Image (cartoon, rainbow over all chains, first blue to last red; front, side):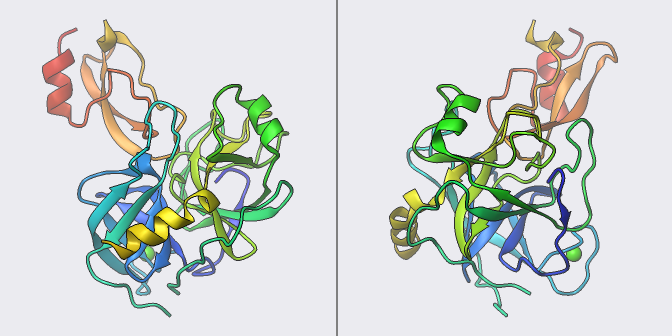
Length: 222
Length: 56
Ligand SMILES: [Ca+2]
């Protein structure tokens, strides 16, 4: 998160860290046994870390749980990044509660809606600086047209842009899979962008409201 | 020669550690890969990297 602020210990209880010997992606707890993240974050041997603030020191509020299953959307396209969504089943259920799940949306959010984006990703746009604690960012959802003008022929109906055209505030490497929460509902998943916090290049996110049926049914038959 | 190309992080936001052959140093080094659109000078281990690009 570039241009954000320290969230505060366990103030984003649905935020999880995907660990493979080190933090590599974020994700959201939507059920005591399920986590939603990005399809490009798919990896073998994923350990999910819940109740985290400082990802480098054990503060006692954590729960480390291995993933038993990792389901990448059947239509995920690694070239176009369309359908960049994945569900991770926890090997055992988490104890909810510093750890809590986030609700799925009843409907899509409109341009202008202010959302909270969080993660342990890079905090520098022209550099490298990874935080110990969780960073937060309030950014508004942008219109489909501006999103499409920022990335010509790259935006699908399953993606939405959020952020600031001026730049300086954005998600970055290490934030992928993390939540974009608006009005207490999970509306997006950190996905891709051109560089980080660049002007006229806002971050692109997976439009969660388009997958609610798939999510509910997939969780239920696995 | 893809072994001579600089490492490519790509547009995705993940922070995945990969290896690339650094021809100037004559060895495989680590770099942060974003998770999508990898180029060929991107390996999962130093052994794979040395096997494919070593001495290029
Ligand atoms: Ca910790």
